[PDB]
Length: 203
Image (cartoon, rainbow, N blue to C red; front, side, top):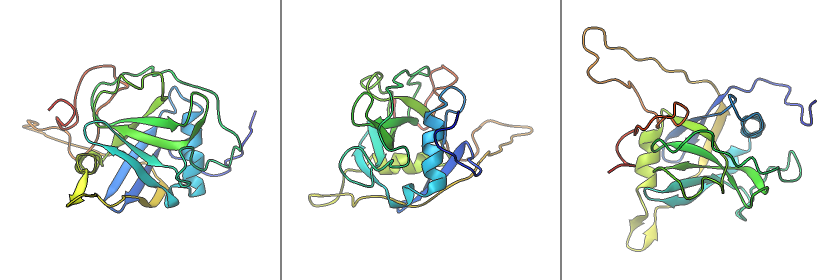
């Protein structure tokens, strides 16, 4: 049964090129059949190309989206708001947890946010189903900043160009893989084990 025909290719991963850099993230097509479709649908639409980061709290979370600036975003493709899917099957393992933003329990919209630390204060307030990749350093240097100068907050960062495309990534260390993790990427809440991307959530 199809309420909204995508009729296109929706990669499980998308890249958001912002005024600061690029933020690549994926949706949980694994466990969240709604959330993955919602973000993907708006991605292949071209909704993020007019969205901005509205809430940037250091070591907290970074809310991104809401083209309207009212707290519920656009999301006019499905008309109304969607049921409360509030159930983090994953856990706040570290920083880099991509979650879905909403104005109420079932007032879920097309907005999202990334957590700079293990968020247990929104476990049942925001449905969490996402993973950030190859952009955690940006999310870090963007989430840690509050002011640009005097008493002026860091000028609003927005998503300049956003397109759905699968970034896999590949590493290596034949003979001495002392490092590990060639590139960027947040923590993995899907593996259900505690680990941090770059210490920012534990330090």
